[PDB]
Amino acid sequence: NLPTAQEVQGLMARYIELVDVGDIEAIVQMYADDATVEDPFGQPPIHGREQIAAFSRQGKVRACLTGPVRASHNGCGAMPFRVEMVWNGQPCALDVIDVMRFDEHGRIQTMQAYWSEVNLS
Amino acid sequence: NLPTAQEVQGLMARYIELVDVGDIEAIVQMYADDATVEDPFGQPPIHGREQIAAFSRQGKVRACLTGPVRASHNGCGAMPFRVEMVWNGQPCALDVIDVMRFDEHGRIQTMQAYWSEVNLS
């Protein structure tokens, strides 16, 4: 576990903070070297920092926290946020919620994004 | 899985319609007899429609959805909601995030809630 509920909220808030300013470098540093990521949740996961840096690098998108971050007592958290993009010259929003679990060193050991087309406005 | 993206949205937003009113018997009917519930996430789990029945009644109270349900394609969902109450003569909100998987029959086969004091206002 390690990170306290109040810490999770801190970490998770920042993660959406780096995603906005587009700091591919910093995000990947919050992840564990052997962290996993299913996004859209369900889909096969991309494990490890390089693969996690490939997707992150691969996909003018702005991120926003639409609600408080829900932190648990065992190092987990979940936050509501929304990504504004542009469907090829067609400004579209995406509502997402990320469910992260941190390790004893305060690193995202796993992340799962919940979203689909029904969340695309 | 089974319930499509749109289906799952409704079933989830349906669940919050029942908590707000207070219908415990309809609530305990979405859950499959074998379902389990981790609430708050990080706690030992509660197995059986039976025990969830005891827990439901266990907790004046109105749950409002705070934003879209994030729905996947493998019969899963995630939603942000607030739960107003008055803890010991002092009103107080609770911002929670529930994640639930539905089996083929559209019954909540598994559920986990994300909250803690850091989300009580």
Image: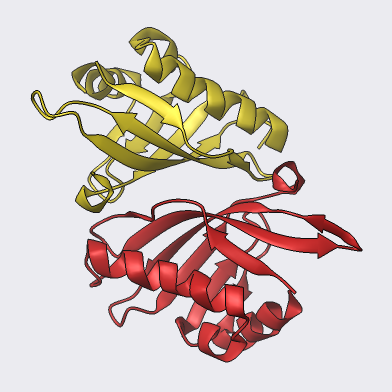
Chain colours: A yellow, B red
Question: Which quarter of the figure has residue A29?
Answer: top left
Looking at the picture, tell me which residue is in the foreground, A80 or B49: A80
Q: Quarter of the image for the N terminus of chain B: give it.
A: bottom left
Tell whether B10 sits left or right of B16: left
Image coords of residue A89 (percent x, y) = 9, 23
Position of B81 relative to A97 (above/below): below
Tell whether B3 sits left or right of B90: left
Looking at the picture, tell me which residue is in the foreground, A111 or B62: B62
Position of B28 relative to A66 (above/below): below
Image coords of residue A39 (percent x, y) = 29, 39
Image coords of residue B6 (percent x, y) = 24, 64
Residue drawn at x 34%, y 69% as measured from the top left: B10
Tell whether A91 sits left or right of B43: left
Q: Determine if residue A105 is in view.
A: yes
Question: Which quarter of the figure has residue B108?
Answer: bottom left
The residue furthest right is B89
Image coords of residue A49 (percent x, y) = 35, 20
Number of marks: 0
Residue drawn at x 51%, y 70% as measured from the top left: B16
Tell whether A85 sits left or right of B20: left
Residue drawn at x 81%, y 57% as measured from the top left: B91
Q: Determine if residue A104 is in view.
A: no
Looking at the picture, tell me which residue is in the foreground, A1 or A100: A100
Question: Which quarter of the figure has residue B30?
Answer: bottom left
Position of B20 relative to A48 (above/below): below
Residue drawn at x 32%, y 31% as measured from the top left: A83
